[PDB]
Length: 114
Length: 84
Length: 57
Picture 1 (cartoon, rainbow over the protein chains, first blue to last red):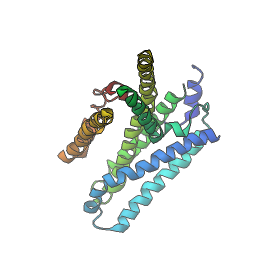
Picture 2: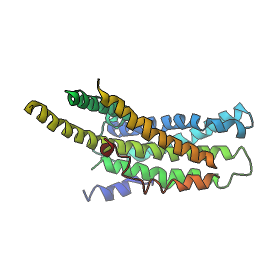
Picture 3: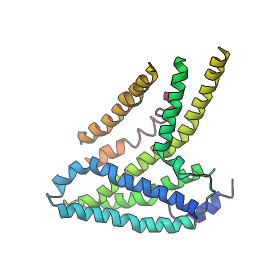
């Protein structure tokens, strides 16, 4: 939910580029999702947009504009939130670590036949 | 300490407000066939967002264990081959 | 020969990814919105700890 600090201050007692690093991790996640499943759902556009490209642009603008008003809201809710710098945007990316898993599992494979 | 909190804070962020916002809005607009677009197009958006992040935040929560096990698994097999 | 790459392709994508994608796509094609979009919220809660990468490794 909202009001991070009220929860967070109540959380971090029983245990800005860094905050921005978390922030841009949302942008990578919320924009790739905004695209990747859009074409997975694009085959339904034609039958219910009534063959109108302007309506396709209308939903794209609205599905966007409804996000930055929250992206600005999440930006102002994340700056006021505080976190320790133990997160790297490179690590949270799956492709960087999936490739590292590929290297690790492959290195486990060459020695396996050795 | 902070990885799980960030994972839990963000999954609860969408599930408590943003996902219901798309869900509640879609419950009204079903007569106008075009108004079916925006809110379920919005529903498919956060619903899958929570779908892959839980497949991504858990991915880093398992790949730091699976690879750690695999790096562990790499040790005794190296401790085997060197011993061989 | 490195048969591990071929076997890893078979059990990673050829087996698991196919069944997951086919389940989602076909059950989506079975429809209306509510029945399929809810009946799968309880499959995550009871098939959990079965798609973790470590144990399928």
